[PDB]
Each structure stands twice: as structure tokens, then as C-alpha cells.
Amino acid sequence: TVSEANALLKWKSTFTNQTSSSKLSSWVNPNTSFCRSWYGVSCVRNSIIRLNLTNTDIEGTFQDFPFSALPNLSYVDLSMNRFSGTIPPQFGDFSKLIYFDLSINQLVGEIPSELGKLSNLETLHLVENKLNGSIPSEIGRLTKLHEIALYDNLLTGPIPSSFGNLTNLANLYLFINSLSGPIPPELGNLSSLAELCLDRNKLTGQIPSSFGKLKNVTLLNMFENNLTGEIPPEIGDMSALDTLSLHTNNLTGSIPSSLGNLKNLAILHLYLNKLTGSIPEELGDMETMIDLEISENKLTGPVPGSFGKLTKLEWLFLRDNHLSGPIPPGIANSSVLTVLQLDTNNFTGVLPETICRSGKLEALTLDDNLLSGPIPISLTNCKSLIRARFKGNSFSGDISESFGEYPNLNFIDLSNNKFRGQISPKWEKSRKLVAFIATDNNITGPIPPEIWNMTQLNQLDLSSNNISGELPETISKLTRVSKLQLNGNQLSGRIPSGIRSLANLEYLDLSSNRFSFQIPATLDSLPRLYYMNLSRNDLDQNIPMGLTKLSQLQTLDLSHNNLDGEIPSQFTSLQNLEKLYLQHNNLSGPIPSSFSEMKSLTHVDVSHNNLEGPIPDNAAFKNARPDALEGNRDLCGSNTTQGL
Ligand SMILES: *[C@@H]1O[C@H](CO[C@@H]2O[C@@H](C)[C@@H](O)[C@@H](O)[C@@H]2O)[C@@H](O[C@@H]2O[C@H](CO)[C@@H](O[C@@H]3O[C@H](CO)[C@@H](O)[C@H](O)[C@@H]3O)[C@H](O)[C@H]2NC(C)=O)[C@H](O)[C@H]1NC(C)=O
Ligand SMILES: *[C@@H]1O[C@H](CO)[C@@H](O[C@@H]2O[C@H](CO)[C@@H](O[C@@H]3O[C@H](CO)[C@@H](O)[C@H](O)[C@@H]3O)[C@H](O)[C@H]2NC(C)=O)[C@H](O)[C@H]1NC(C)=O
Ligand SMILES: *[C@@H]1O[C@H](CO)[C@@H](O[C@@H]2O[C@H](CO)[C@@H](O[C@@H]3O[C@H](CO)[C@@H](O)[C@H](O)[C@@H]3O)[C@H](O)[C@H]2NC(C)=O)[C@H](O)[C@H]1NC(C)=O
Ligand SMILES: *[C@@H]1O[C@H](CO[C@@H]2O[C@@H](C)[C@@H](O)[C@@H](O)[C@@H]2O)[C@@H](O[C@@H]2O[C@H](CO)[C@@H](O)[C@H](O)[C@H]2NC(C)=O)[C@H](O)[C@H]1NC(C)=O
Ligand SMILES: *[C@@H]1O[C@H](CO)[C@@H](O[C@@H]2O[C@H](CO)[C@@H](O)[C@H](O)[C@H]2NC(C)=O)[C@H](O)[C@H]1NC(C)=O
Ligand SMILES: *[C@@H]1O[C@H](CO)[C@@H](O[C@@H]2O[C@H](CO)[C@@H](O)[C@H](O)[C@H]2NC(C)=O)[C@H](O)[C@H]1NC(C)=O
Ligand SMILES: *[C@@H]1O[C@H](CO)[C@@H](O)[C@H](O)[C@H]1NC(C)=O
Ligand SMILES: *[C@@H]1O[C@H](CO)[C@@H](O)[C@H](O)[C@H]1NC(C)=O
């Protein structure tokens, strides 16, 4: 005691970067008050049994720790400090030790195999250190152990097979490590095991079939390993499982139908594997299933209609598989299903009428399938919708009658379909909507003026449709639009000067349209614009000087128009211009020879114009092909088609 108090003081005398305010100030008067007023210290019959110095800013090492002087120690918590160095083998000499915690420290080196001498240990905690090497096999001797936590370390080698002998172990936490080799099948002997967390390691081999005897395990985390083979059907015998996470592995083969037997399983993560074959119909017998994610695999065949039996399903992640056949109505029938992602599959047929029958669905993805037919009515009136993606399908129908008002809509993508009809003004009710993309449809009619009132819109893409009419000056109301694509339509009249107001605009494409008359001269107020495709239009007259005030312009394509006159000398203030396509115009006269000052011009086409004179000094003109520079009236000082 009085010896113990001196020993601990001699240890405390080695701590560095200590403060007068340290909680260890109370380590005073060893002769009288060791067992009554010292912080961390606690005694029985006047001998220290409990040292709890957690989070006391102690900086130091365990070298001069008085192992021999504190024999009756049975509770050591030195966690959340700045301890460094190694774990001396004398820690195994605390024959009475029950709880041992050195976590959240800066300890280095291996784990002394002398820890297996601590026969009375019930909890071992060494997490969040830089301990390396392999886990001592003698730790399998501590058969009173209830919980082993070695996570967030640099441990390597395999999990000791001796750990099968830890018949009282309930929790094994080995994640964030570099453990390797196969999972020892003796882990199946852990009848008392509750949580097994081996995730985020470099484990390999197959999942031991003896895991089926782990009848008390409720959490099995083995994700982000390099496990191989197939999911053994004996995993279906782990009846107490509620969370099974095997994702980001290299597993193969089929999904065992025995997984249906897991009546308490609420989370199943199998994604990012190489699983093949059909999804068994027994996976619908997972009555507790909340979050099923088997996306990003090689699964084939149809989704079992038995998925209507998953009445607690909330998240279904089937994306990036080779699933096929029609989508069964059971797959969306859940009253609580809020995320149904099916994109990047080979689904055929039409959408089931059950899609949003309960009005709780929020995320729906169907990108890159072989679907067709109309939008089901329950989806038309699915006011809860937040994210919708229909890209790359053959959906048909009146785009005005197919889509009701979505107040909660945030992102919808109708690209690459066969939608007909006119854009309804109902989309204005989606006041939180920020991106509207409907490329490559058969949409016709005018853009309703309500669309410009949608100020929250960040991205608007109506390209490759058959939309007509003249753009109103109220287009200036799109304050926050930054990607604007109306190209590939039959919009007509002049270009509205209101595009001057879209200051956030970055990428603007109005090409392949029927815009005619002069480009608005005022258009000098787009400081974020790095792209302007006005090509393949009917625009005629001088290239306005306002375009030369668009500093950040990287690409500028005014090709296939009726522009005339000379290329202005004020292009030089577009120092950041890289690609510039002015071909197939009626431009006249020479370049001012200030194009040498401009540098980043690499791809320039000035073909089929009435210009004359010599090409200026920059790469693109030297690197131009015959087609790039052909067609002009008097090309080059020495009538050249290629270099000088
Ligand atoms: C387990 O880790 C220890 C400690 O390694 C140290 O801590 C890690 C968290 C990393 O930051 C390492 O970069 C860091 O070194 C390893 O022992 C260490 O071995 C190296 C040599 O491999 C030692 O460096 C040498 O130190 C001597 C002593 O002055 C010099 O003469 C040499 O020139 C050289 O600098 C290092 O001191 C040593 N650290 C110790 C013993 O605490 C150990 O090898 C490793 N085991 C593995 C990876 O299996
Ligand atoms: C040293 O003393 C500290 C403080 O008493 C001990 O930390 C305690 O550790 C337990 C471990 O579970 C914490 O229990 C948890 O408490 C929360 C509510 O705080 C509860 O909701 C959880 O279910 C859980 O039981 C406890 O909070 C925590 N106390 C503090 C103040 O952080 C530490 O365990 C002691 N170590 C030794 C060896 O005596
Ligand atoms: C601005 O938009 C226009 C179209 O609205 C883009 O111009 C043209 O796009 C077509 C795409 O099919 C190109 O046609 C094809 O070109 C290849 C080239 O090898 C040719 O082999 C095919 O037979 C076909 O003609 C066309 O070249 C292209 N024209 C230009 C001038 O690019 C244009 O690309 C868009 N602007 C930018 C900067 O991309
Ligand atoms: C291609 O352009 C030439 C150039 O004419 C321009 O006309 C003005 C717009 C102004 O920019 C002038 O500096 C240019 O000369 C067209 O040739 C003109 O055609 C008109 C007939 O409408 C005639 O009155 C002019 O005298 C012509 N100019 C010259 C120099 O001959 C030409 O018609 C244009 N071709 C196409 C297909 O658009
Ligand atoms: C603290 O440890 C000491 C030994 O380091 C224990 O002292 C022994 O106690 C037993 C029975 O109480 C005696 O037979 C021995 O002769 C004692 N040895 C010494 C060197 O004193 C002491 O009992 C322990 N106390 C607690 C509370 O565990
Ligand atoms: C296990 O699967 C992973 C997939 O995440 C593989 O990691 C990829 O390997 C290839 C190169 O061989 C590339 O696609 C990437 O460089 C890797 N990382 C990815 C895709 O994130 C890993 O090689 C597989 N292990 C095997 C087959 O033993
Ligand atoms: C004490 O803290 C300072 C500041 O972080 C650090 O530079 C130093 O290495 C620490 N240790 C000693 C012995 O000064
Ligand atoms: C587990 O304990 C038994 C008991 O005798 C022993 O024979 C066996 O070798 C132990 N396992 C390992 C891997 O050492």
C-alpha cells in the first residue's frame, strides 16, 4: 500500500507534458491517503485493486510501470491517453486481473503472448492503437473472456484457431485490421458468441460451414474482406441473426435458400460480390427483413414474386445485376418500402400497379432496363417521391397525364424514353426540384412559362426533343440554373436576352435549333460560363462583342450558322479559351494577329468561311488538318494547307 503508493508515484514522475491542473494532483501523502483520496485508485483491505485513469491526459510509457508492486490489481483502465511504446510482458503477471483496457492510445508493437497468463481476465480492450504482428495464440487460454476488442489496429496474420476454446466469449471485435488467411473453422465452437465482427480486414478463404452452429450470434459483420467461395447454406442455421453483412467481398456461387430460415434477420448486405444464379423464392420468408441489399452482383433470372411476403421491407437494393423477366407486383407491395432501386438490370415488361400503392415510396431507380408501357397510376399520384430515374427505357405515354404533382421531388430523370405530349405546368409545384432531365424523348409543344418560375432549378435538360416556340424573356428567372440544355429541338425566334441574367450558368447548349437573327449583343454577364454551343442554328450577322467578356469560356461552338463579318480582335480577353469552332459561317477578312496572345487554343475550326490572309501563331493552326482550315477565300500568306 504505502509501497504501492510510492511505486505509482515513481511511475507518475516519468509522465511528460503534464499540467498542474492534472487530475493526478491528488497523488499526495502516500503514507496516509492512498486508498481514500487518490484519483483513479481504489482499494480492498488497503491494497489497490482498481486503477481507472481513463482520459486523464497522461503522456508516458509503461516501461517504468510498477508491475511487481501492484499484485492485487484487477481493474486496469488506462484508455484515452497518450501512452506510447509497447505492452510489457509483465502485464500478464496480474494474476487477479479481470478487466484490462489500454484502448485509444498510441501503443506500438505486438501483443505479449504473456496475456494468456491472465486466466481471470473477462474483458480485453486494446482498440484504436498501432499494435502490429499477429494475435497471440495463448489468448485462447482465457476461458472466462466475455468480450475481446482489438479493432482499429495493425494486427496481421490469421485469427488464432485457439479462439474456438473461448467458450464464454460473447463479443469478438477485430475490425479495421490486416488479419489474413482463412477464418478458422473452430470459431463455430463459440456457442456463447453473440456478435462476431471481422469486417474491414484482409481475410481470405471460404466462410466456415461450422458457422451454422453459432446459434446465438445476432450480428455477423464480415464485409470488406477478400473472402471467396460461396455463402454456405449453414449460415441459414444462425437463427439469432438479425444483421448479416458480407458485402464488398469476392464471394461467388448462388445465394443459399436457407437464408429464408433466418426469421429474425432484418438487415442483409450481400452487395459488391460475384454471386450468380437466381434469387431463391425462399428469400421472401425473411419476415423481419427491413434492409435487403444484394446489388452489384451477377444474379440472373426473375425476382421472386414471393417478395410480397416481405411486409417489413423498407430498402431494396438490386441494382447492377442481370435480373430479367417482368417486375412482379410483390416487389413494391410493402407499406413501408421507401427505396426501390432496380436500375442497371434486364427487366422487361411494364411496371406493376403496386409501385407506390402505400404513398410512402421516396426513391425509385429504373435506369438502363428493357421496360416499356405506361407509368402506373399509383406512381402518377406518388406525392412522396423524392428521387426518380427512368433513363434508358421504352416508357410511353402523355407526359402531362402520366405525372401528377410531386411536392417533395428533388431529382427526376426521364432521359432516353418514348414519352409523348407536352410539358405540363405541374412541375412548378415541385418547388424543391433542382434537376429536371428529359433528354431524347418525343416531347412536343412549348416550354410552359411556369418552368422559368422554378428558381430552385439547378440543371434543366430538355434536349433532343421536338419542343417548339420562341423562348420568352422570363427565362431570366432561372437564377440558380447552371446546366441549361435546350439543344436538338425546333425552338425558333431570337435568343432571349434574358439569358444574360443566368449568372450561375456554367454549361449552356442551345445548338441544333431554329434560333435566328443576331446573337444578343448584351450577352456579356455569365462569369461562370465555360461552354456555349450555339451551333447548327439560323443565327446571322456579326459575332457580338459581348461574348468576349465571358472570361471563363473554355469551349465556344458557333459553327453551322450564318454569321458574317470579321472575327473580332477582342477575342484576346478570352485567355482561357481552348476549343473554338466557327466553321460553316460567312465570316470575312483576317484574324487580327492578336490570337498569338491567346494560348490555350488547341482545337480551332474556321473552315468554309470567306476569311482571307495568314493564320496566326498558335498550336491549333499549326496542328490543323485540311478540313479544319479549308474553304476560306485566301488562306495563308503562302497559300498553304499545312504547316507554314
Ligand atoms: C511493429 O511496429 C514496430 C514499431 O514501428 C514504429 O511504429 C509504427 C506505428 C510505424 O510508425 C513504424 O514506422 C515505426 O517504426 C516495429 O519496430 C520498429 O522497427 C523499425 C525498423 O524496422 C525501427 O526503426 C529503426 O530504429 C532503430 C533504433 O534507433 C534505428 O537504428 C534504425 O535506423 C531504424 O530507424 C523502429 O525503431 C522499431 N520501433 C520499435 C521497436 O518500437 C516492428 O518492426 C513492427 N513489426 C512488424 C511490422 O511486424
Ligand atoms: C472507469 O470509470 C469510467 C466512468 O465511470 C467508466 O466509463 C463507463 O463505461 C461504461 C461502459 O459501458 C459506460 O456505460 C454506458 O453508459 C451509457 C450512459 O452513460 C449507457 O447508456 C450505456 O448503456 C453504457 O452502459 C459509462 O457511461 C462510462 N462512464 C463514463 C462517465 O464515461 C469505465 O468503464 C471505468 N473503468 C473501470 C475499469 O473501472
Ligand atoms: C454542339 O452540338 C453539336 C450538335 O448539336 C455537336 O456537333 C456535331 O455532333 C455530331 C454528333 O453526331 C457530329 O457528327 C458526327 O461526327 C463524326 C466525327 O467523326 C462523323 O464521323 C459522323 O459521321 C457525324 O458526322 C459532328 O461532327 C459534330 N460537329 C461538331 C462541329 O462538333 C458539337 O460537337 C457540340 N459541341 C461540342 C463542343 O461538342
Ligand atoms: C455571304 O456574305 C457576303 C458578304 O456580304 C456582307 O454583307 C453585309 C452583311 C456586310 O457584312 C458586308 O460587309 C459584307 O460584304 C454576301 O455578299 C453580299 O450579298 C449582298 C446581297 O444580299 C450584296 O448586296 C452584297 O454586295 C454582297 N457583298 C459582297 C462583298 O459581294 C453573300 O450574299 C453571303 N452569302 C450567303 C450565302 O449568306
Ligand atoms: C494483496 O497482495 C498481498 C501479496 O502481495 C496479499 O498478502 C498476502 O495475504 C495472504 C492472505 O491474506 C497471506 O497468507 C500472505 O502471507 C500475504 N503475503 C504478503 C507478502 O503480504 C494480500 O492479501 C492482498 N490483498 C488483497 C486485498 O488482495
Ligand atoms: C475482389 O473484388 C474486388 C472488387 O472490388 C477486386 O478489386 C478490383 O480488382 C480489379 C483489378 O484486378 C479492379 O477492378 C480494381 O483495381 C479493384 N478494385 C475495385 C474494383 O474497387 C479484387 O481484385 C478481387 N479479388 C480477387 C478476385 O481475388
Ligand atoms: C510535448 O508537447 C509538445 C507540443 O505538442 C511536443 O512538441 C513535444 O514533443 C511533447 N513532448 C515533450 C517531451 O516535450
Ligand atoms: C483447445 O483446447 C483443447 C483442450 O485440450 C486443446 O487440445 C486444443 O489444442 C486447443 N486448441 C488449439 C487450437 O490449441
Image: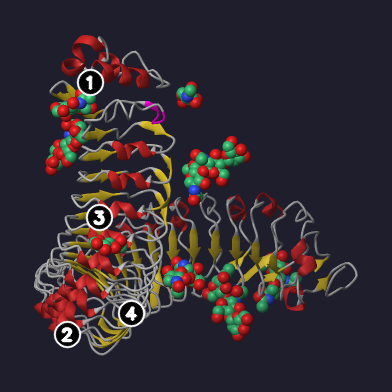
Question: Which of label 1 and label 2 is nearer to you?
Answer: 1
- Mark 4 and mark 1: Cα distance apart in space: 56 Å
Q: Which residue is mark 2?
A: 281
Q: Earlier in the sequence, mark 4 or mark 2?
A: 4
What residue is rendered at 18% in x and 23% in y?
47
Horizontal side of 397 relative to 555 (left or right) equals left
Q: Earlier in the sequence, mark 4 or mark 3?
A: 3
Q: Is mark 1 within 8 Å of ligand 2?
A: no
Residue at disc 1, secondary structure: loop
Q: Which residue is mark 1?
A: 39
Q: Position of residue 179 (x, y in %)?
A: 39, 59
What residue is rendered at 32% in x and 49% in y?
150
Q: Which residue is mark 4?
A: 275
Q: Position of residue 242 (x, y in %)?
A: 15, 64
- Mark 4 and mark 3: Cα distance apart in space: 27 Å
What residue is rendered at 14% in x and 70% in y?
289
Q: Amino acid at mark 2?
A: Glu
Q: Quarter of the image containing the C terminus?
A: bottom right
Q: Quadrant of residue 77?
A: top left
Q: Are marks 4 and 3 in contact (CB under 8 Å)?
A: no
Residue at disc 4, secondary structure: loop
Q: Is mark 2 within 8 Å of ligand 6?
A: no
